[PDB]
Amino acid sequence: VLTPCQQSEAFHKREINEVRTLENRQANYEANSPSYLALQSQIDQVHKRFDKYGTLLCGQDGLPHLITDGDWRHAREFTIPALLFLYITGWIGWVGRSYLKYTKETKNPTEQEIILDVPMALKYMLSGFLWPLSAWQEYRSGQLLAKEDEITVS
Amino acid sequence: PINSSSLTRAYLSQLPIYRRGVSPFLRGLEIGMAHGYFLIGPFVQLGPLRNTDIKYLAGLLSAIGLIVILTLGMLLYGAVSFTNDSQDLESVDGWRQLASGFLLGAVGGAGFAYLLLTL
Amino acid sequence: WVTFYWHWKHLSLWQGNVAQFNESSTYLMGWLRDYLWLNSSPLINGYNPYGMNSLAVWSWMFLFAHLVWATGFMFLISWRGYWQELIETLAWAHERTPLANLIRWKDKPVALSIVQARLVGLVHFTVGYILTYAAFVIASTAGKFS
Amino acid sequence: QVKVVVDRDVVPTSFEKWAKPGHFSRSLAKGPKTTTWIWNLHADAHDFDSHTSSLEEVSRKIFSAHFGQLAIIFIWLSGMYFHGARFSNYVAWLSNPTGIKPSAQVVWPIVGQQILNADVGGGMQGIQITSGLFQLWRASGIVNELQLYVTALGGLGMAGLMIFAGWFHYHKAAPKLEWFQNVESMLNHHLAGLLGLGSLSWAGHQIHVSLPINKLLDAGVAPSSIPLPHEFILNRNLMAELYPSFQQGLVPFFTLNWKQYSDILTFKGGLSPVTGGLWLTDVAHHHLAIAVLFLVAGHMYRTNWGIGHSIKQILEAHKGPLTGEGHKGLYEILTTSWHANLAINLAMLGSLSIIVAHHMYAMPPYPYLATDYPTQLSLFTHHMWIGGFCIVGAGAHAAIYMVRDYSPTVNFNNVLDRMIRHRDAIISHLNWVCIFLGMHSFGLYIHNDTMRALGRAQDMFSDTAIQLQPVFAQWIQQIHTLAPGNTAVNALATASYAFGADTVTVGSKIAMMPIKLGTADFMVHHIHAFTIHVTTLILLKGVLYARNSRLIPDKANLGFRFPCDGPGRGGTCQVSAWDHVFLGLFWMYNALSIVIFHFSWKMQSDVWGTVTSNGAISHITGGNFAQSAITINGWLRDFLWAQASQVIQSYGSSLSAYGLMFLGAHFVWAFSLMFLFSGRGYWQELIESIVWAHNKLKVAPAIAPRALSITQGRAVGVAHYLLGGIATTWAFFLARIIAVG
Amino acid sequence: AHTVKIYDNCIGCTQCVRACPLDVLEMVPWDGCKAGQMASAPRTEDCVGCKRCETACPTDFLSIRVYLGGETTRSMGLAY
Amino acid sequence: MITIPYTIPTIMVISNLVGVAVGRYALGRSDLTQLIASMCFGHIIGVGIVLGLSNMGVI
Amino acid sequence: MNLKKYLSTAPVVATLWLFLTAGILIELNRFFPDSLFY
Ligand code: CLA
Ligand code: CLA
Ligand code: CLA
Ligand code: CLA
Ligand SMILES: CC1=C(/C=C/C(C)=C/C=C/C(C)=C/C=C/C=C(C)/C=C/C=C(C)/C=C/C2=C(C)CCCC2(C)C)C(C)(C)CCC1
Ligand SMILES: CC1=C(C/C=C(\C)CCC[C@H](C)CCC[C@H](C)CCCC(C)C)C(=O)c2ccccc2C1=O
Ligand SMILES: CCCCCCCCCCCCO[C@@H]1O[C@H](CO)[C@@H](O)[C@H](O)[C@H]1O
Ligand code: SF4
Ligand code: SF4
């Protein structure tokens, strides 16, 4: 059963064990060593690390699990970086497709791919920002796809 | 060309095959007379029965245990190849008498080595 | 991966520590540490310079099947024409030597064609693979129990 | 005669041809219609005897390229001196070296990886050095951070002189070929000028820097009371206290009363019992012996003054009867073909690097080097590995000579091709020696494996069982015990403490123990002779069957990196002189993997470890070699199962980056097999079946996406098999010995 | 024998015969192309089957297609 | 190094003169390099004789 | 003059873009480390 992670026992056992275990090296230095300040910053980055995983679900393992159902209580877990990611490589993919359908109609398409025309490249890098309703409106013209390309025997 | 000299030819020419005329039972009996005395050796000192008093008999039984495979392969080689009947070593009958000579001379060499592990 | 996964699941049930699995199976050193290194301990102790026990057959089969699995790579990696121009050197070495050029072959010595080469490398890959893992399943679970 | 004719303003220095990739090859300036142009661009980036047959233009290209290599090496050593300066704990390491583990690289604090900063002491953390730079700096006498900063900045200065030198010697002053075929002068200046003045000037550094400094650090002086090497030459008085022969000046030198220089120079050998290194009196005296001996050696090549040899009149004079013509032609081979010179120099360079490894483990020449065992291990191992690879470079570039630059007119009945007349008798007897040593080097291991597995340990090859005590190595090692009284008359101790007397300990750490060789060490030496003979088989089969085999009688008409001929002759895959080098790299991995698996486990059983009260002994595995190296289950269990345990449990600690470079190197090793086993007849229409999925969405790439070629599609399997295979033993070894030593 | 067949795409550029190091291939005057030539393989008893012809066959797709057939002494290319 | 009576420079000039006696033979031209090469060789021989004479026995 | 063509090639712009997005990941993981939400 996925307990809420802020109250799970083995979670806070890992809190005591890692703050104490990393803290064992912190007594190897004086009060004004640069390493001692670095492990001050590291202990801060462990208490923040465990307070910022409060609303997750760590089960009996004491390790924060995830949920990928789109439950809308786990939306910040999976689906918000899911839609975020699909926007980012939809950006990248529409940039690359748009640049290849640029260099397909140029003088010499071979030299276009070694030496990227950074004018027209950085045109398409930035212009491919709104690929759902630009790739979709280039799909409604019947132009994202193709037909009767290369194939083997049958 | 080189390693083809007259000392090479004079050593190879009187070997127990390249010598001119010997009956194939004796021509193989010389081969077995050497090898049967040989193969007793690497079973007495290094064999598994070097710990009991069967140090010397296990060389006989193990070595003839090789020799039956050796003459068996001799009969396979003269059985498959050397099809004609020119009656010499390149035949069937001369090769199987070469193999029988190697067997009887090999077992005789085994008994000679066994009776010379006495002294 | 299927039978490694099943086997490291039921070695965690039968020993009892399922928490040993669930905490240490989502990273690869959990597998290689907590399963292969730990559970080959009764396998690889199958015979010592101190002595042996009943699992010496499975550890001897274990090392054996690593040798099979690595003789596969001699055929899979290193293809024919190396050996097709090396069996010619051996055939010169037998055609030219005295006391044995009498014993000449009937079927001519030819390196294995590459339909066969990738096959026999495949066969030693499977025999070595499957005998290694049948050595490890039985030596492992027979070592943690019985 | 000797004269230097130099073309000026050879090549203009605009960035125009950087915009033309593949400008250099007219076979490749067509531009990429396929993606194989991308990889052929890099496979022809240094085929200098494939750009143009004109050896002048080639020779300018290579000779300018060497300065680029030395520029990268001076950037590398300036990097090591700066990471010694700003980032290392070397100043604190100089106080107590046996307690403080050496660290330079201080990992930047991003997510997690700040835990790699190992608290190695010195008050400052960071990942631990295994390269052994601090031992060479204590030997060289670098006291504080200032010489590391300044020597780093001089490293960048020489890097600028090598970039400017290479630009200067390709573009605006580049020589003729008559400068290059003036080779008696080249030997005449490299034997004498490079190595002679190198060892002589280094004897200057050791006598006027290291002998006072590593006398004071041998006396245990803190690195603040130590004066600068500066201050030992303003007056002889600070050195006459340390070495009282400096008071006499150079006067006993010029009167040849060299008995007086027993303070500065001696012949003692052994090791320093305090620092665990060689006596720098012996090492400075040694570099004087290389000094006078190489300056003698340089002057045997007639250049302008009609005094000295020429190589032609030497090689003609050995007109032996069993070779017929003698060495006629080799001065014309080695001064017209670069690849043959690269074969010789990579063979002797690689075998020198192996010699370096074997001379560094047993005579540890740096102070406190044998104390920290990871620097003792990895400087054996690293120089063993480059010392391996360079021999395969000999086996490749010998074949690149034999395919391209062979000409039977200059090379007719001499010592060279008379081998190739009986190359069947060369390769056939290598074939026999390989089978005989394989049976008698590994069949003994299957024997002891079975006899230990069959219970009958009375039938093994141990000391208790049927022994195989190495007779010859123990006898000559016993001669090396009896050297310094009998034959090395003016010595005191032996050549090493791997030979003779009782062990040398520094800080309760065993610096060197006399190595015992019984009946298991024997069989591993036959492993090494075996897998050396197999690489010699593949790398002589790669050269004698390079140009015209009896399988394929036109290979020079096909080339060097051709994949094959075809399925004819029943299949002729992998038959080129390159493909034997493809095989010799795997056997390089085998041969050196069991060299270092002999090293790092015999010397974790027979040498290294600690010493306790009353001089009592303790090894790391605890004498667990001769009862365990005889089998393979003892080898795999007691070595690869047991020594892995400090690499595998290394998580949550500073050794966990080796726990990442262990698994990832298993990944790269396993990832090579995809390239080795399959071939482009699969991947080309797998890829083209993906090209359908790009042609459907108009994402057809204009450079056509081929698969790799065959020779690239096996060269990359080598270069992953070796990167993953070598980095496994890398992470295993450094995570083993850092975790204890 | 390794059956060599030479189809009607053979436009007679003769890189095949120059590419065959066995002279199984010759050129035959055939009035169906611009060069008037079309290659022939009469002596396939010596045909190794190394497919060095098919590398240097600049037709549309392989006018000369080598089918790997019989394996004699000569067609296996063994020296001894 | 002592004066005219027998010492280390006494056994050097004999090495120099047998060195140039080699220099009359080893491409015995009468140039500079007969002396600069051959007096150097007899100089090497003289240094090999002085201290090799110093270790085993009387100087 | 033609250096900017060399700074428009495939590997150089590959390093000047993967170096840049690499710096986006590292500079976005120094400022907000341990980011499993959102
Ligand atoms: C122009 C950019 C571009 C675009 C839009 C696509 C799109 C596609 N590829 Mg892909 N591909 C690309 C480049 C691209 N590819 C490159 C450069 C390679 C060589 C590594 C591949 C190798 C490849 C394989 C092997 C496969 C696909 C497949 C696919 C399809 C499924 C999506 C997927 O998993 O992608 C796969 C994505 C990758 C393998 C990694 C992405 C490749 C690079 C890193 C990103 C591309 C950005 C591009 C270089 C930007 C250049 C332009 C810009 C400078 C102006 C989809 C149509 C699959 C398919 O057929 O499904 C139907 C499939 O099996 N691709
Ligand atoms: C005694 C003079 C001398 C010295 C010291 C060297 C030294 C070297 N030569 Mg070299 N060479 C010489 C004479 C000399 N050469 C002559 C006369 C010829 C023509 C016959 C050549 C032909 C030659 C070739 C063809 C090659 C070398 C190479 C090398 C380098 C080998 C790498 C190495 O050991 O790095 C150790 C590095 C050092 C020890 C640093 C050395 C720098 C110091 C300051 C000496 C350099 C002085 C410089 C030569 C004087 C030029 C005069 C000019 C400024 C007016 C090394 C720097 C190889 C190389 O890498 O190319 C550069 C190479 O391929 N040499
Ligand atoms: C572990 C796998 C493995 C093994 C055992 C071998 C073994 C061998 N390779 Mg090799 N090779 C391998 C992997 C392997 N390779 C891989 C992965 C590559 C990839 C690059 C190569 C590439 C390669 C090349 C390129 C060459 C070899 C060659 C050889 C032979 C060297 C001669 C020798 O040692 O004879 C001794 C034999 C052994 C040690 C094998 C064990 C034999 C035991 C000890 C005795 C017999 C067992 C048993 C009694 C048999 C009877 C029972 C049975 C009939 C029922 C040898 C058979 C060379 C060759 O052709 O021969 C010279 C050669 O040129 N190999
Ligand atoms: C190749 C390495 C090797 C070697 C040297 C040995 C050696 C041995 N094994 Mg063995 N073994 C090996 C591999 C090897 N094994 C492997 C790979 C396996 C597993 C497949 C086994 C499995 C095995 C078992 C199961 C047993 C042994 C046993 C033995 C011992 C007795 C066997 C015997 O009678 O020899 C027979 C020897 C010969 C027939 C001699 C032939 C060779 C001669 C010397 C060649 C001479 C030629 C000459 C030099 C030519 C030049 C001179 C001429 C020109 C005049 C012996 C010590 C037995 C034992 O109890 O151990 C004590 C036993 O039970 N072995
Ligand atoms: C090291 C060496 C060598 C080698 C060795 C060898 C090779 C040996 C051999 C030897 C041998 C190997 C011997 C043999 C022996 C034998 C004898 C002396 C004979 C006798 C006879 C017999 C055996 C008989 C038998 C029999 C019998 C008994 C009965 C009846 C039947 C018969 C008749 C069969 C040489 C010399 C080369 C050289 C030098 C060195
Ligand atoms: C997988 C495989 C391939 C396919 C390998 C493909 C063709 C190469 C994949 C890696 C390249 C580098 C991808 C190209 C992507 C570019 C780098 C652009 C990406 C954008 C940035 C990363 C710069 C072979 O061509 C092959 C050939 C012969 C034997 C075995 C094999 C084989 O096993
Ligand atoms: C019979 C008269 C003999 C005189 C001997 C003098 C011996 C030294 C000759 C050079 C004189 C100067 O001495 C040098 O002093 C400097 C420093 O002053 C040092 O190099 C050495 O001591 C001498 O080289
Ligand atoms: S087929 Fe191709 S190769 Fe053979 S001739 Fe016609 S064109 Fe030349
Ligand atoms: S098959 Fe081999 S030999 Fe016959 S033609 Fe084609 S390539 Fe030449």
Image (cartoon, rainbow, N blue to C red):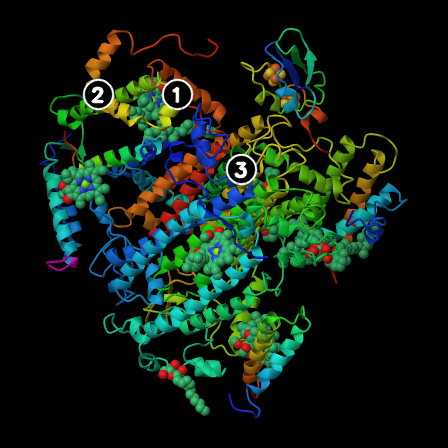
Q: Amino acid at mark 3?
A: Thr
Q: Nearer the viewer, residue G13 or D119?
A: G13
* Crowdedness near tag 1: few (<14), some (14–19) or many (≥20) residues, C-alpha within 10 Å: few
Find residue A25 and report its image quarter. Answer: bottom left
The dominant secondary structure in magenta is loop
Question: Label 2's element?
Answer: helix
Q: Distance of mark 2 from mark 3, alpha carbons?
A: 46 Å
Look at the numbered disc 2 and say if its residue's Cβ is closer than 8 Å to ligand 1: no
Question: Label 1's element?
Answer: loop
Q: Position of residue D317 (x, y in %)?
A: 70, 59
Q: Disc 1, disc 2: CB below 8 Å? A: no
* Crowdedness near tag 3: few (<14), some (14–19) or many (≥20) residues, C-alpha within 10 Å: some
Q: Amino acid at mark 1?
A: Asn
Mark 3 — residue? D52
Q: Distance of mark 3 from mark 1, alpha carbons?
A: 28 Å
Q: Residue at x 49, y 28 (%)?
A: D679
| Magenta highlight on residue A31 | yes
Specify whether F8 is left or right of E3: left
Q: Amino acid at mark 2?
A: Ser
Q: Chain of mark 1?
A: A
| The magenta segment | A28-33
Report the quarter where the N terminus of chain D lies: bottom right
Specify whether C2 is left or right of D349: left
Mark 1 — residue? A108
* Crowdedness near tag 2: few (<14), some (14–19) or many (≥20) residues, C-alpha within 10 Å: some
Residue A127 circle label: 2
Q: Disc 2, disc 3: CB below 8 Å? A: no
Report the quarter where the C terminus of chain D lies: bottom left
Question: Label 3's element?
Answer: loop
